[PDB]
């Protein structure tokens, strides 16, 4: 049968197939199966496809992964990104806002990305537990933009007073749009968490799982693999360290 790969449509609008094409061709070469790219706007919809075994493999975010493990999604590997980054949520405001801490965002307008994002939502929902508040009882209003870049744009435009986003996206955005970056500051950083793992559906065969794991873990030793890695700005895939997501598991329990 077809091997179905699921991603969010909101990471790279108009450029998803452009970015994933080479890794999909690699999976065709390593599996001998036709590969179909399945997009959804929300991480909840992607997780439902995994849960119902409607797809084989998914590139999901870190909080999605923590929920997906509970219904038997299995980790394949995690990207080791060029610069070997560390992953955290950053809270950004405008430098000219006079809002210089998370505390000073009480009764302000705040942007989240996707409800199932750690860096775009859950990191800050987890944090607010310490003061027995939720985003709804801490902020004057909240909005789910479904995009780290749009959240960043909304802070820049004064539509919201702050946002929580992926530190990787903030870094890349400062380089590509330095005039936007210069207007913004990080007022708060989350604890470190692992990179988002690639997962397979609970229904995928153990044989297909071992093939897929070997294909990912050896991708940097294959010519088409290197082209797939270059195109995604990943140096290689490495084994999952489950401990790297324990902070997310703990937050999720405090709800």
Image (cartoon, rainbow, N blue to C red):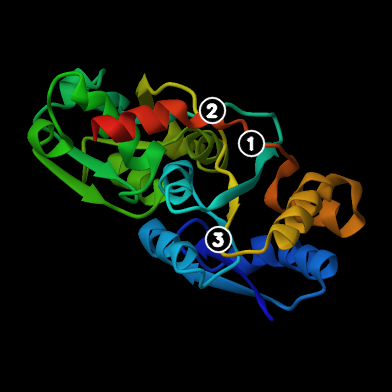
Residue 211 locus on image (x, y percent): 78, 57
Mark toward the start of the polypeptide (3 vs 2): 3
Above or below, 159 relative to 102: below
Q: Is residue 184 visible?
A: no
Label 2 sits on a secondary structure element that is: helix
Residue 4 locus on image (x, y percent): 61, 72
- Which disc number belongs to residue 244? 2
Verify CB contact (< 8 Å) between mark 1 and mark 2: yes
The answer to which quarter of the image holds residue 137 is: top left
Q: Which residue bears the numbered disc 1?
A: 240
Residue for point 54% across, 72% down: 38
Residue for point 74% across, 50% down: 213
Above or below, 234 relative to 228: above
Q: Which residue bears the numbered disc 3?
A: 201
Q: Nearer the viewer, residue 53 or 143?
A: 53
Label 3 sits on a secondary structure element that is: loop
Q: Nearer the viewer, residue 182 or 40?
A: 40
The crowd level at tag 3 (other Cα within 10 Å; few <14, some 14-19, many 20+) is many
- Report the side of 193 relative to 23 (left or right): left
Mark toward the start of the polypeptide (1 vs 3): 3
Q: Nearer the viewer, mark 3 or mark 2?
A: 3
Q: Is residue 250 visible?
A: yes
């Amino acid at each position: 049968g077809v091997f179905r790969v699921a991603v969010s449509s909101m990471i790279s609008p108009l450029e998803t197939m452009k970015g994933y094409g080479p890794v999909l061709s690699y999976i065709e070469q390593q599996t001998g199966r036709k590969v179909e790219l399945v997009q959804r706007r929300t991480y909840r919809e992607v997780n439902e496809l995994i849960r119902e075994n409607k797809i084989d493999l998914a590139f999901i975010c870190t909080y999605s992964f923590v929920e997906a493990e509970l219904f038997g999604a299995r980790p394949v590997a995690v990207p080791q990104v060029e610069g070997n980054p560390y992953y955290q949520a950053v809270v950004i405001t405008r430098r000219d806002s006079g809002i210089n801490s998370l505390e000073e965002l009480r009764n302000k307008r705040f942007a989240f990305t996707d409800p199932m994002s750690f860096s775009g939502h859950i990191a800050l929902r987890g944090e607010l537990v310490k003061v027995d508040r939720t985003p709804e009882t801490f902020f004057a209003s909240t909005f789910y933009t479904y995009s780290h870049d749009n959240s960043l744009r909304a802070v820049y435009d004064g539509i919201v007073d702050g946002a929580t986003i992926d530190s990787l996206v903030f870094r890349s955005s400062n380089i590509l749009y330095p005039e936007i970056g210069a207007a913004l500051q990080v007022v708060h950083v989350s604890p470190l968490v692992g990179a988002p793992p690639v997962v397979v559906s609970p229904g995928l065969s153990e044989e297909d799982y071992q093939l897929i794991r070997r294909a990912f873990l050896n991708m940097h030793n294959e010519p088409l693999g290197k082209q797939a890695l270059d195109t995604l700005f990943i140096d290689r895939f490495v084994m999952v360290n489950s401990g790297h997501y324990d902070y997310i598991r703990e937050i999720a329990g405090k709800i």
